Amino acid sequence: DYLPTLRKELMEVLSKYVNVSLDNIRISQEKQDGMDVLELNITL
Amino acid sequence: DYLPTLRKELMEVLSKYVNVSLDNIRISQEKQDGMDVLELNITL
Image: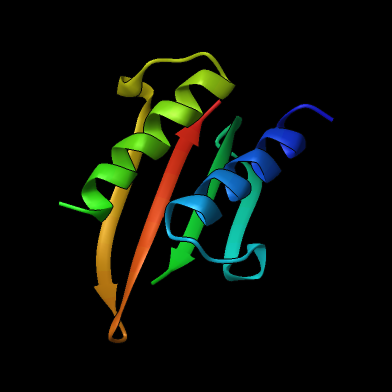
């Protein structure tokens, strides 16, 4: 609900920075070592 | 000049989403397989 939405928001912001589409952007939400870590990747 | 700036911009946007500081955000710019891949990480 919360972060998942913010993750989409991050994608949109990035797509505007390098003027690509959302299909070229990947973002993952994972729980490791007890913590919730977001990872946002893009290939240019 | 270009992406390095956008990388900082990404950090700022993320810090506002989860209302943290820039010190809790990491972002890397690396060349792998001939391509330039940005990686933005945050621990929550």
